[PDB]
Amino acid sequence: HGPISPIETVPVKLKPGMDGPKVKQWPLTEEKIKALVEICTEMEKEGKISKIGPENPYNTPVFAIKTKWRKLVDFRELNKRTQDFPHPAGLKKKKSVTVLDVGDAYFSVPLDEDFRKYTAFTIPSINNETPGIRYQYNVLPQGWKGSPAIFQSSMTKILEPFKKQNPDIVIYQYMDDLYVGSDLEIGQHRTKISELRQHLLRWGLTTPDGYELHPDKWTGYDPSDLIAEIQKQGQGQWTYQIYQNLKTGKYARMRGAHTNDVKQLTEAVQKITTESIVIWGKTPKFKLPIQKETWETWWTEYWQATWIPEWEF
Ligand SMILES: Oc1cc(O)c2c(c1)Oc1cc(O)cc(O)c1C2
Ligand SMILES: Oc1cc(O)c2c(c1)Oc1cc(O)cc(O)c1C2
Ligand SMILES: O=[N+]([O-])c1cc([N+](=O)[O-])c(O)c([N+](=O)[O-])c1
Ligand SMILES: O=[N+]([O-])c1cc([N+](=O)[O-])c(O)c([N+](=O)[O-])c1
Ligand SMILES: O=[N+]([O-])c1cc([N+](=O)[O-])c(O)c([N+](=O)[O-])c1
Image (tube, rainbow, N blue to C red; front, side, top):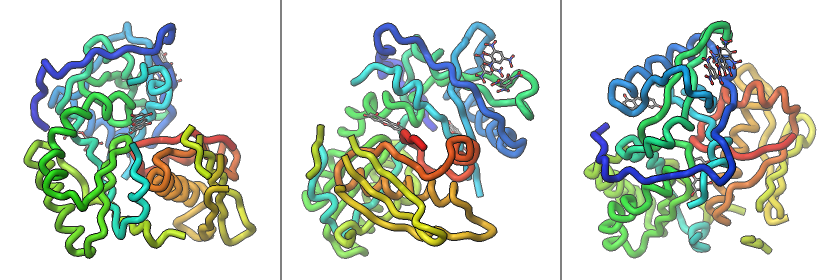
């Protein structure tokens, strides 16, 4: 991950009269702690985070998810506290839409030195019995709402040659993802995705393989909040409603040695969100058919998105 440019540092503020977040770190398995220690040691060596002293009172929770492990930060409270900074109706009509995570970009952009204290986090000790290892970010963090806002002018400059050369392709950005849609034959669409990823890479932006959607095959919206309600429909399936119904659907509810309701609900939350972004450009608030304590206990075991939505129970 390349070096940062000090002149790209952008001042950023909390909302007036709000202090930084102090959300405690929940306990992690020793396997997850080891993984985070390894990740954070590398980030620190590369200047992306720094160990902090005893004066800093803020905290944002972190966890680890998977072959390899990735660090996930729950910035929901910092996001609420951070200052504030069009959706194509045709995206859902495209033969293919590939979702590309472009959050790697953020490691190459500095965070306002005065704001870094609000990104503090702790790698926990085993059982949270002794003080953890405290760090803060020096670069735009993934999951923070300021990061895509601050990176937007560079993202635009980077994408411009691709968009100019491909008027048949729609590119929509939402949070840290690009949604790249076309009506090309799947092989030709995939070639365009590869050209895009190679262009990003040329400018220092690595991407994982993208996720492919085919929304033209999917089954009154007020742009002025989306609610997604999932309910148990007996022993064997899930139903859901999206309303402000705008959409309803179903998923299988399976029992087995490698699944459970929390795992299935995290999957359905991700899929409903992705579909809602494609169709309307908005992330729903969720109502989940599970007890808070059970959810709060296990959702991070299976969560795969970089983003984390709001949910009630
Ligand atoms: O979620 C993850 C997982 C990783 O394995 C890594 C992450 C983040 O961030 C960095 C940043 C660096 O600048 C250099 C690195 O090696 C890594 C590894
Ligand atoms: O990985 C994440 C997680 C979030 O929660 C958010 C992200 C990215 O990006 C944005 C961008 C905006 O322009 C406005 C937002 O509220 C958010 C929230
Ligand atoms: O989890 N936490 O919220 C948390 C917070 C602080 N602190 O200074 O604000 C800690 O020192 C530790 N700690 O060291 O374990 C944890
Ligand atoms: O490691 N840690 O993240 C950690 C966290 C907490 N906490 O309540 O959130 C602690 O009280 C302690 N502790 O007491 O050592 C450590
Ligand atoms: O020692 N500690 O484990 C510890 C833990 C927390 N905490 O919120 O979990 C703190 O806020 C502080 N603290 O602020 O000093 C210390």
